[PDB]
Length: 154
Ligand code: HEM
Ligand SMILES: [O-]
Image 1 (cartoon, rainbow, N blue to C red):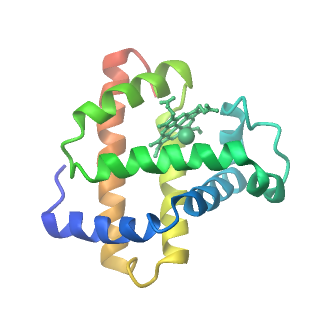
Image 2 (tube, rainbow, N blue to C red):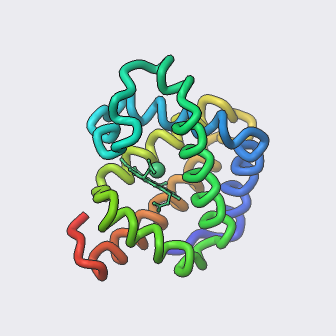
């Protein structure tokens, strides 16, 4: 699939607000993912012991992880679909090292949309949410194809 430039601009205008405080947005996204789909926390060997939202919020390592994840995703979005180089290493680590099914990529995509809808009504109206869903679907579609090339079902 292919996004229009207008759609990419709606994605990048909300991402500019995320970048005001990437750490805080990453904590909210993880808290939402782990609360909504608790099975996903089991994939993180360093964090799977966390029991409550308060513990998740206080984890300096989880906060650092969130920054890494949103910064990598932000670099993919800024390529506006020309993200083959960025997707290579990520697909390899997520298929082979971490073993993250496509379904769990759908769960984190849902969590990102939920947090942007909550924090950024000014830049996350219906058209902008639609454009971000398209961008994240494109990301998952391209990751899934790479998973298959790498020998992972997903
Ligand atoms: C937007 C989708 C995602 C992005 C951009 C992303 C990005 C990253 C990056 C950049 C790293 C560090 C380098 C690497 O190992 O590749 C990482 C590590 C990791 N990712 Fe993801 N990730 C995503 C989704 C997920 C999901 C949904 C899960 C699990 C349910 C997951 C599980 C992990 C784990 C377990 C690690 C190792 C963390 C640690 O060092 O403790 N990832 N991810
Ligand atoms: O992650």
